[PDB]
Each structure stands twice: as structure tokens, then as C-alpha cells.
Amino acid sequence: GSFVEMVDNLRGKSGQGYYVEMTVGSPPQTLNILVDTGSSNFAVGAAPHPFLHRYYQRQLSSTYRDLRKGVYVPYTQGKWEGELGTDLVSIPHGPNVTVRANIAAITESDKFFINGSNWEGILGLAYAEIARPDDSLEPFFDSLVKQTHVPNLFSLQLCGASVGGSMIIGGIDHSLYTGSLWYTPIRREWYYEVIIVRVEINGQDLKMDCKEYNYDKSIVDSGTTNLRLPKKVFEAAVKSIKAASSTEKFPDGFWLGEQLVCWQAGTTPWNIFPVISLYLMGEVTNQSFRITILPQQYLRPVEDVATSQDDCYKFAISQSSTGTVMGAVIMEGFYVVFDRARKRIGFAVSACHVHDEFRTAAVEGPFVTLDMEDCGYN
Ligand SMILES: CSC[C@H](NC(=O)[C@H]1NO[C@@H]2OCC[C@@H]21)C(=O)N[C@@H](CC(C)C)[C@@H](O)C[C@@H](C)C(=O)N[C@H](C(=O)NCC(C)C)C(C)C
């Protein structure tokens, strides 16, 4: 076992991603690996770095094999190259197994590792199709399901505020969410690609073309902090959120994520910021459901030192050229099930949820929505 053992096995720093503990090689070297659903490559720093307090020493693993190949992985921000090998891997606070998994040893990286982040590697939980340099490179989870009896499914429970959560590998832990799970189809098994059929702000429809929401694509990426929207959608929402908050004033560099906002501690005017409702395509015909986001999610907190401590937040909705990204701020407060087996993603209200005083982040269905297929971009 056991699910209770995997609960609370993620840790993080705010806006710095969630990591889990893994071991690589024999004898086992323990490293903190960022859980990333927007990528398909298992990689760790194998070289010294100013931002790393640990790294993978293949020289110290009787089990390391070399694929005599090199790889380069770009991300929306940050990139790295290294040497492909295969070693033995285990998750201390996950299923009780060890598997031979492809591993990229990171030899050189730009804008990838984070100063003070406690993670020295990344675990791409998406599919092979987006693996580098090709789908030949079985991704970790594929290896794990192919070499064990771990079911082909995992759920992520990302709790905010430093920060922690749970990664239940191979099942659903029912003590971690309330209500019922709602499922949206994985449109295609490359990214975790979902179809957003409608968007509402404070109960008002943005009334854009369904396609605009998934222009390029929409994905669930635990590895991206913000909620990232296509240009057109993004602009619409900012306009909407601005109007909802015109009572106060902020630099338009705030809405760009550049500047910061602070209020006298415990004085945050949550009420003037709206809720955002994302309607995801459902499991039956003409059926969808919605998840509702509180400003406590897209207003991310960031500590600043001041003669008065205050409460400071960064605007956590960013413009995108790669499609919509349902990042960690969206995933926080929900229990998200990556049902790779039944080709779907389920959402429920997390046990560790947002808890506004007069508003609740919710998962609600059923909703009827016609021509939902017309929302996928082609
Ligand atoms: C400026 S947008 C922020 C996002 N990273 C972050 O927010 C983070 N910065 O510090 C923290 O680390 C993770 C969370 C925090 C990011 O850009 N990128 C990555 C997370 C990092 C761990 C490398 C990925 O999760 C993004 C993911 C969608 C991705 O880029 N996947 C690649 C891709 O699809 N395309 C490559 C791209 C240049 C077109 C792989 C599949 C190869």
C-alpha cells in the first residue's frame, strides 16, 4: 500500500511548483522531483549548479545504463539538455515498487531551476507523444504501469498556503475530496488536453466563440503556476476583472503580473474580485459541468518585508500564445484525477479548499451545452 501513505507527500514554495521525493540508482539517491503534467520527460540535475543542493551522480549507481543519446527539452519558460540513461527509481511515499525508467541527466540548463526551490528534477506525467526527442522514450508513468500492477491513473491534490499536497499514484483517495467527481474527456493523449466550452465571470458569459477558449489547445499543467489564457480570452477576462474591481486602483503592470498589490493585513477587498467559471465538456451528449474559481486562487500571495507586514498578491492570470493552461492556481482547491485508463480528467472540491467567507469554489453539474464539439480548435 497505501493511499494514506501517499497523502501529504508533495511539498512546495508558493509559485515555485510542487515536488515529490524519489530515489534513483543503487544505492538510492533521494531527490526532490517537480510533478509536472505539462511535460513527458523525467529529468534530474546531474551536474553542480548554484541553485541545486543535490544532483544525480550516475557514477554512484551500480544500476545506471547509458542510452548514448542526448536530449534537449524546451518549456514555456526554461530549457535544458542532458544525457539519456535508464536507472532504477522508487517513490518513498508512493506505491511500494521500483522500476527501470528513462532518465535525462541535466548537464546544462537555462531558466529552468529556481533559486531556493527545493526540487532538483522534473517528472513529466503527460504522454509519450510530447516526449523528447520522440515518443520512443517511454515516460516514467508509462514505465511504472507497464512494469507493475499500479493502475493507470493518478490524482493530484494541490493545497495552497510553505505549501503542500498529495499525489495519489494509482487511485482515488475519497477522504481528500467532498461531493462527486466530474469528468471531462482527455481530447487526445499528448498533453492533458481538455475542451473548455464556456467561460463565465461573476455569472456573466464572456460570450466569445467557444473556440477562442481552446485556441491552439487547453491543458491541465500542474507545472505552470498561473492560469494562462489565449490573447483574446485573456483580454476579455482582464477587462471583466478590472470592471469588477474598479472601486480600487492598481498599476496596469499589476494586470501584467509585473507589479504587486498589498493591503493592510486582513483588509483584502476580496468581494470586489469576481469568480471565474470554467465549463468543461462532460461525459454525455450536450452535457458539461463547471468549476468555479475564487479570487483567492488567481490572486496569489507573495510575502514582502515592511514596517507593516501587509498582505501582498500577484495577479496570477497571464496571457498565452500556446493555448489555455489550467495551472496550479486553478488546480489548488480541487482534487484532480488523471484517469489515463478511462481517458478523462475528474474534478471535485478539494478537502483543502479556498474558503471565502461568503463564496465557495465549486464543481457543479450537469449543465447542458450544445455543439460542444465545435469548441476544439483545428
Ligand atoms: C512562464 S509560465 C510558468 C511555467 N513554470 C512555472 O510557473 C514555475 N516557475 O517556478 C515554478 O516551477 C513550476 C511551477 C513554477 C512554465 O513555463 N513551464 C513548465 C514548468 C517548469 C517546471 C519548467 C511546463 O510545465 C510548461 C509545459 C506546458 C511545457 O512547456 N511542456 C513542454 C511543451 O509542451 N512545449 C515546449 C514549449 C517551449 C513550446 C514539453 C511537453 C516539451
Image (cartoon, rainbow, N blue to C red):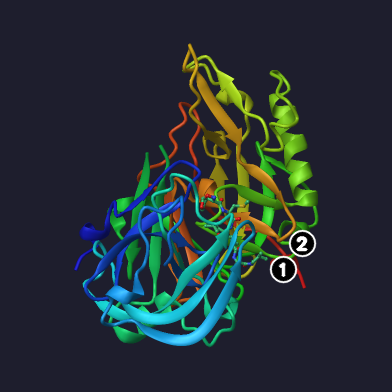
Q: Amino acid at mark 1?
A: Gly
Task: Pinpoint residue 12: horizontal percent, then vertical percent.
Answer: 40, 47
Q: Position of residue 353 (x, y in %)?
A: 41, 41
- Is residue 149 toward the left or the right of residue 68 in the image? left
Q: Secondary structure at mark 1?
A: loop
Q: Quarter-wise, where is residue 315 in the image? A: top right
Residue under the point 29% across and 55% down: 9
Assign ligand 1 to one image quadrant: bottom right
Q: Residues within 10 Å of mark 2 (few under 14, many from 20)?
A: many
Residue 82, x across and y down, in percent? 51, 73
User: For the point 73% across and 22% down, which residue is it?
Assistant: 246
In this rendering, the answer to whether 319 lies above or below 139 is above
In the rendered image, the residue lying farthest to the top is 307
Q: Which label number is shown at residue 211?
A: 2
Percent x, y for residue 347? 47, 57
**Splitting the image into 4 quarters, where does residue 192 fall?**
bottom right
The picture quadrant where one finds residue 23 is bottom left
State yes or no: discs 2 and 1 in contact (Cβ < 8 Å).
Answer: yes
Indicate which disc, 2 or 1, sits on the residue closer to the N terminus.
Answer: 2
Residue 146 shows in this picture: yes
Which residue, given by chain and number where applicable, does mark 1 sit on?
A: 376
Mark drawn on residue 74: none
Query: Front-most of 284 and 361?
Result: 361
